[PDB]
Image (cartoon, rainbow, N blue to C red; front, side):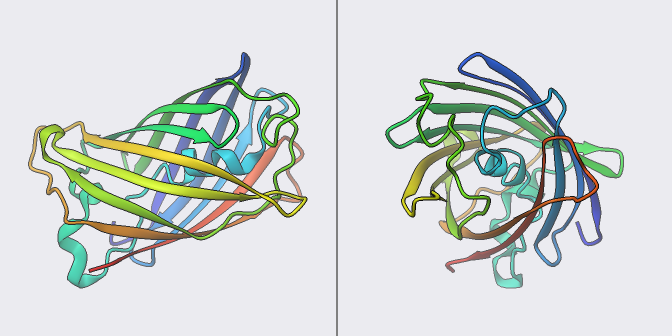
Length: 222
């Protein structure tokens, strides 16, 4: 992770029966804590607004967080490489439905690959998610990481705030658990967080339903 590593993202999902697939490619720079991704919906029109997938694909790969020198001891993500780790989540949108996600992150050659299955249920058809009322941007968060010795992994907790067009804010509770795939020693961390910032852009020469994602993540709190 000292250099620039290519990324591959594969997502197969169905939210309230609408099946969709999303494929993306980009590169992460852990040294500077940067991520860039172009993600494209291959099945046509995305049932859900793009920001709701930012965490799934984007916060999907968190190896590329920049852990400062005095905190390098707590970096589970890089510590689990190259065998990889499993990333499981329940994302519950307040007063609406629920994402439940299983993802595997590992190296396949010089490339890091993020493979996800997503299944969402109980969404209002005129609610903020299925009716596409979310603004095409993303807010700044704190991913609170904590150790789970019993599962030899970590747990994560954060509240994502999705800006709504009318000025309101759609809250999304993330409950995340990570487990390493490899038999080796991974170090399980003291309490800390990952402060995240994101911008969401467009490729003008891309006409398929897509999103261009930038992430900026640095660890803090020790």
